[PDB]
Image (tube, helix red, strand yellow):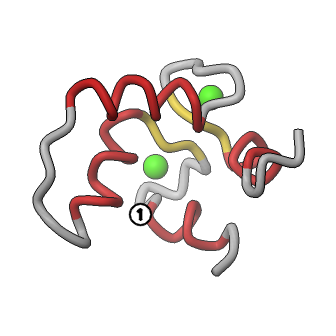
C-alpha cells in the first residue's frame, strides 16, 4: 500500500531491485514461473532498466504518474 514495499523487499538495503528481486516479490505470494512476464515486467517497472529498478524510478512508476 505504498513504496516502502520496494525498499522493504530489498534486504540488501541497496534501494534497487533487479529482475530477480521482482520475480521474488511475487513469488512470496505464490509459485508462478513467468520468463516472458518477468522480462517484460522487468523493463516495464524499470524506468531506465539498468540491471535493476531504483527506488526513485519505482516511486515515479507507481501509479504510472510519469
Ligand atoms: Ca535489493
Ligand atoms: Ca535501475
Is residue 13 found left or right of 36 in the rendered image?
right
Q: Is residue 28 above or below residue 54?
A: below
Is residue 17 found left or right of 37 in the rendered image?
right
How far across and down, in percent of the image, does residue 60 sit?
82, 47
How far across and down, in percent of the image, does residue 65 sit?
88, 48
- Number of numbered discs on residues: 1
Quarter holding the C terminus is top right
Q: Residue at x 64, y 73 (%)?
A: 4
Q: Residue at x 30, y 38 (%)?
A: 20
Check disc 1 and report the residue beneath it.
11
Q: Is residue 49 above or below residue 41?
A: above
Is residue 14 found left or right of 65 in the rendered image?
left
Q: Residue at x 39, y 47 (%)?
A: 22
Q: Under tag 1, what secondary structure?
A: loop
Q: Residue at x 24, y 69 (%)?
A: 28
Quarter holding the N terminus is bottom right
**Mark 1 CB near ligand 1 (8 Å cut):** yes
Is residue 45 found left or right of 61 in the rendered image?
left
Q: Residues within 10 Å of mark 1 (few under 14, many from 20)?
A: few
Amino acid at each position: 500500500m505504498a513504496e516502502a514495499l520496494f525498499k522493504e523487499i530489498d534486504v540488501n538495503g541497496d534501494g534497487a531491485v533487479s529482475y530477480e528481486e521482482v520475480k521474488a516479490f511475487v513469488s512470496k505470494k505464490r509459485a508462478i514461473k513467468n520468463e516472458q512476464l518477468l522480462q517484460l515486467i522487468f523493463k516495464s517497472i524499470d524506468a531506465d532498466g539498468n540491471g535493476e529498478i531504483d527506488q526513485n524510478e519505482f516511486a515515479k512508476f507507481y501509479g504510472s504518474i510519469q
